[PDB]
Image (tube, rainbow over all chains, first blue to last red; front, side, top):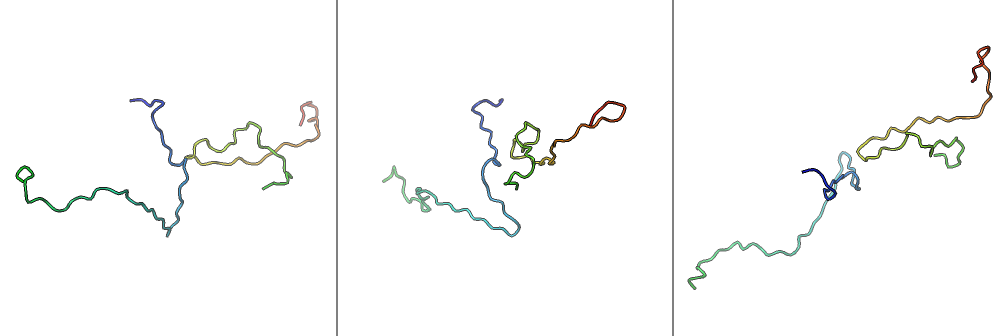
Length: 50
Length: 50
C-alpha cells in the first residue's frame, strides 16, 4: 500500500502544544457522555421459563 | 531589532538563508554580512581591480 491523496500524514509539531520544564505540571480533564451502565447483578430466572 | 533600518537590509534577496521548511528542523540563522560602495583601486601593474 503506497500513500495516496487520501493518505493522512499527520505532523504533530505543526500544531500548538505545551512545553513543560522540570517540575512542570499539566492537567487534562474529560467528561464522559451519558452511557448505559453495566449491570453488576445477574438473573435468577431463564427468560424462556417465566 | 533594527526598527530604524539603520543597518543594511539584506533580507528578501532570494538567498539560501530561510528558516527550515519543516517544523522538525533546527534553524541555523545566517551570518549577517552586507555590501557597501567604495573606490575601485587598480592592483599595481596587473590591471586587476579591487
